[PDB]
Image: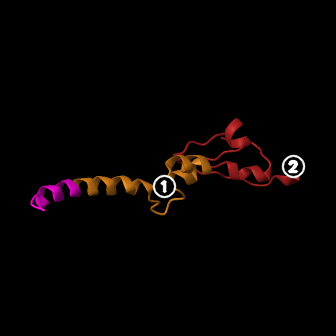
Chain colours: A red, B orange
Amino acid sequence: DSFVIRGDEVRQIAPGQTGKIADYNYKLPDDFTGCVIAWNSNNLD
Amino acid sequence: SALGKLQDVVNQNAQALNTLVKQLSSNFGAISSVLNDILSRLDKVEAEV
């Protein structure tokens, strides 16, 4: 599952979280089995 | 004082049940012993712990 977010929002990409990204966009289940991988693509701008 | 044996059995039953109910008020290291506090003061991940 793949997307771009602001760096401060990356902490919301975890099971059972709450906040705008975790509530209105991409919610991981409380028993999620998986890996979350992220990097600042800041040179893209 | 004659019926001490039967009154002791009634007292032990009441003492056991009151002890079992009073233990609902204990924290056991939790943030509160009121379960609705835990479910309202915390996010679901911390609340489950």
Q: Is residue A34 visible?
A: no
Residues at marks 2 and 1, CA–CA distance in whole angstroms: 51 Å
Residue situated in front as seen by the camera: A31 or A33:
A31
- Residue A32 rendering spot, x and y as whole percentages: 54, 46
10 Å neighbourhood of mark 2: few (<14), some, or many (≥20)? few
Q: Is residue B18 visible?
A: yes
- Residue B5 rendering spot, x and y as whole percentages: 11, 59
Q: Which residue is mark 2?
A: A44
Residue B3 on the magenta span: yes
Q: Which residues are magenta?
A: B1-12
Q: Amino acid at mark 2?
A: Leu
- Residue B14 rendering spot, x and y as whole percentages: 26, 53
Residue B7 on the magenta span: yes
Q: Quadrant of the N terminus of chain A?
A: top right
Name the residue at 63% across, 47% down.
A17
Number of numbered labels in the structure image = 2
Q: Which residue is mark 1?
A: B33
Name the residue at 54% across, 45% down.
A30
Question: From the viewer's perspective, is residue B40 above or below residue B19?
Answer: above
* Left or right, residue B32 beside residue A14: left
Which residue is most to the top? A24
Mark 1 and mark 2 in contact (Cβ < 8 Å)? no
Q: Quadrant of residue A28?
A: top right
| Magenta stretch: dominant secondary structure | helix
Name the residue at 53% across, 48% down.
A33
Q: Residue A17: which disc?
A: none
Residue situated in front as seen by the camera: B36 or B4:
B4
Name the residue at 16% across, 56% down.
B7
Q: Numbered disc 2: what chain? A: A
